[PDB]
Image (cartoon, rainbow over all chains, first blue to last red; front, side):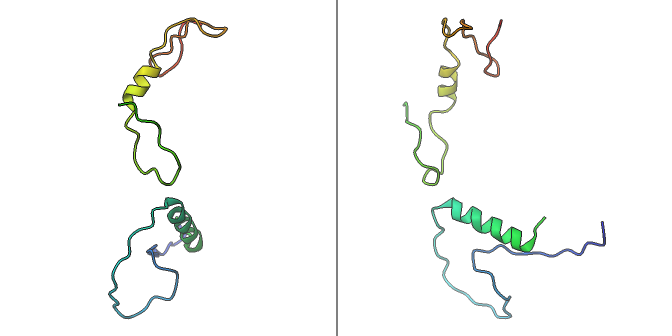
Length: 52
Length: 50
């Protein structure tokens, strides 16, 4: 409803910033063993993006 | 094989080994305990004949 326009927000592990027009390849670091930090980051990114 | 419950909320990222056996053991007491007495909790885990 209300002429919705779809927007996709990629909640990658990297910090929020302007999307760059250049492919950068770097080695992936191991995931943090604390899931609470990941949950808080996901919640903050969703709130900022207003993800439905 | 009675593994103690895991400690912590972030370190534990697996289900406890003491699962269905622990539930079956817990839902196996049949005595006269408490004011109601005759603890016969079965099926979903609720007593009978109150």
